[PDB]
Amino acid sequence: MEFVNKQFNYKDPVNGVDIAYIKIPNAGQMQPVKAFKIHNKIWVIPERDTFTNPEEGDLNPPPEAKQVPVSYYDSTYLSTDNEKDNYLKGVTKLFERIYSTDLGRMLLTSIVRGIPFWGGSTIDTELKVIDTNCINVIQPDGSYRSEELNLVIIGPSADIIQFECKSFGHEVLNLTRNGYGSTQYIRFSPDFTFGFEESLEVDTNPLLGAGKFATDPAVTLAHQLIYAGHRLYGIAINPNRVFKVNTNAYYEMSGLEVSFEELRTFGGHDAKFIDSLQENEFRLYYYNKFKDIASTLNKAKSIVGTTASLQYMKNVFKEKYLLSEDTSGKFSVDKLKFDKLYKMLTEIYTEDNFVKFFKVLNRKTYLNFDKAVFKINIVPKVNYTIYDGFNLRNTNLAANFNGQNTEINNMNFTKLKNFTGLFEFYKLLCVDGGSLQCIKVNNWDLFFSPSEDNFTNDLNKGEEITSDTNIEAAEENISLDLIQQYYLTFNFDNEPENISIENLSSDIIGQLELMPNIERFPNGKKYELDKYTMFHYLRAQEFEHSRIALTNSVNEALLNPSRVYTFFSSDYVKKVNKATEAAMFLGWVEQLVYDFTDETSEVSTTDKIADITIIIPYIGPALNIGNMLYKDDFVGALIFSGAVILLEFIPEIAIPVLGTFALVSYIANKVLTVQTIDNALSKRNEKWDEVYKYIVTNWLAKVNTQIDLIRKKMKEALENQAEATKAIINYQYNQYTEEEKNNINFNIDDLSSKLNESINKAMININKFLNQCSVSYLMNSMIPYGVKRLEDFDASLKDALLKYIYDNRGTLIGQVDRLKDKVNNTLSTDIPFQLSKYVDNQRLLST
């Protein structure tokens, strides 16, 4: 123990201090629930949540199917003392795991300091607690006392693997969006986790194992705490701000509900989907909310419902909001300290950064959707530790995230049935009109495609440059060094003491926050197409797990369920389809492993594209890129038109005529005229940086996302090939009569392992290629439209400033040539584009 300085057993008796039956805010009445206080301001309740929502009482699968990639239902889970005990030890262990990291130590500390604001009075000269931020703690003698708290962890409602962060609302105030904060209830379970597919970590790991991987539940809990942090500090982005997707095209998703907050909280490339304009909008919005809080602290003449003094309570909120105070005692919001605190909560505390600290395998995007659900047990030390998670040191599970590999570490992951059917939410893609060849494509296997309305700019808007024009210091890049800098400003003692309040009504009446009405997206929309598609080519490579598979080179594999499509050569099919005599089986399998490697490790080298040095030719026939077909045709297609060929949809990238600067002059004041010129020149630098950041934003959301899904499909295609080949080989083995056992002695697992190495080796090359395309399209097809407008702008500012200096040669006299040289040198050179200035992540940065 360390963060949880207590080693609870569920059955331990009640004491009314850290083990007690409690009453939480509720729509009407609830019977007390036995709860545990694991740490100051933080409680845990080992019950399924049938309390927080009056609508969520039943624990069964709902009548309406629910449009999520993964879900799980079992009304029996968490109803025994034994399960409750294990939940309590599970949640505890995850807290300790989060606390062992520098990042987690800060976040948990931030959480404890983030006391919800005392803004419950209708009289604005008083500080009063808001009741729904408290709970009632039953005593052994039957009586109760009320207590403030910041965080409650409760078991999930009906859908066992829907982890979410809920809190109670107010009649007039928006507590999670006004700076105040409110006590957060996290529905969470440490007894289940998600299965997902990797594609992005093989470069740093050639030896990565075969199938699905398991999310470390410490990441899942951290993510939720990050949400909780935002709402505790009342700076959460309105849930009405969401990423709207286009849905009408055949390759697009039928729908997706991602919020700004969800993407902000993940971090990584996803956070950069949110354009600067809205980012400045949100920061400025919460700045003002903090300002209002300071005012209210200055208005306060009294405090009700506690024995703590006004002075102590004013000090608590000064400490939370990092307010400064005069010697007279006036509280204020310093713009510098705010920006630091808001960045810490907003951009330092992200899911992507925790993964850096946990050293686990994890999704690199929110758009990498969960695929499976697993039963887990993280309590035994031999399963999962505070220090390594599943990947225990000095064990087979230490390297290549093996302990997270669902196949190698099968003792630890039991697959459960996904209650969301594979083709429950889908589009129907058909090719030829009386006869049709139709395939269902899972909603979440389709393309992202954000709508144009999510991206805004004021690049067209003009400006006046004065000697008083604000120059903003360049944004300090989010990195492990910045996090280190913030870690050193923490002082890990002096958490706000558990002050006693007067008792509330024994039933705390509260409603959860609105949660906006969101209509189900349409389902099973049919599409009639003339040409096969990426999805068709992919489906053709699958077979049924009547048993004898055969490989072939055309999509009529979509016709026979016993023929499977391969993008491998005609030579390879002859060999793998060839019926093989027993005395020659081993030599056959060995040669097939070499052939498989030769087919998958193909790399064409070029100097004809620029920003693209390698080309993997088989991506052409593997996913039907451009439709044209043929490997040597694909290299030719790529060389002719560049990276665009890979995209399913071409983004629009319209940069308007950039707003020009009008300069103000100051007759006979040399110094202020000098400042106007400098402020104009540094404002051009800002303008360049702004167009670059805007283009990058667009590129990440509309382009790089397409490539991200294209590597997933490439890993699928490869996996499909290895399965077809294995099936074929195993069928061949199974035809021999007992000349198998003593003589052949064939290990299908060693084969499966060899093929997995090839797939790994191939994906290294595929990642290199797809990154190059991605960056290439940015550099050649998007950035040039930015630079063009910026060039026109420099020429305008050049003329303005050389005229301005001439018209003020009377005022400037001392140094007109100096300033004339400064303008000529600054504006005759483009500000060069550095990608590391605009992405914090490391992939696509090597390139």
Image (spheres, rainbow, N blue to C red):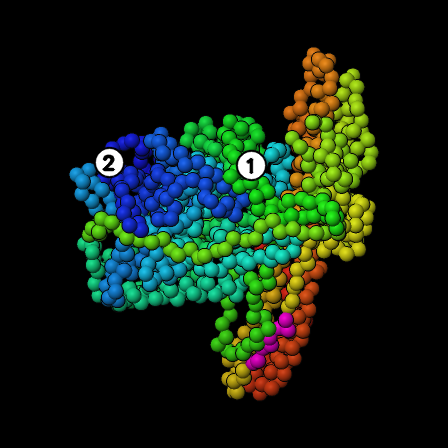
Q: Identify the residue at horizontal 26%, vertical 39% (top origin).
A: 20
Q: Is residue 458 above or below residue 548?
A: below
Judged by its main secondary structure, the magenta piece is loop
Q: Amino acid at mark 2?
A: Val
**The magenta segment:** 656-663
Q: Horizontal placement of 398 versus 156: left or right? A: right
Residue 414 visible somewhere in the drawing = yes
Residue 14: numbered disc:
2
Give above or below for 153 relative to 645: above
Q: The N terminus appears in which quarter of the rendering? A: top left
Tell me if residue 563 comes above or below residue 119 in the rendering: above
Query: Are there few (<14), some (14-19), or many (20+) residues within 10 Å of tag 2?
Result: some
- Secondary structure of the residue carrying tag 2 is loop
* 605 left or right of 23 in image: right
Q: Is residue 639 left or right of residue 157?
A: right
Q: Residues within 10 Å of mark 1 (few under 14, many from 20)?
A: many
Q: Residue sitting at 61 percent across and 79 percent down?
A: 801
* Mark linked to residue 213: 1
> Under tag 1, what secondary structure?
strand
Side (left or right) of 194 relative to 38: right
C-alpha distance separating marks 2 and 1: 40 Å
Residue 312, label in figure: none
Q: In this rendering, does residue 108 appear at all? A: no
Q: Amino acid at mark 1?
A: Phe
Residue 657 sits inside the magenta stretch:
yes
Q: Residue at x 45, y 44 (%)?
A: 62
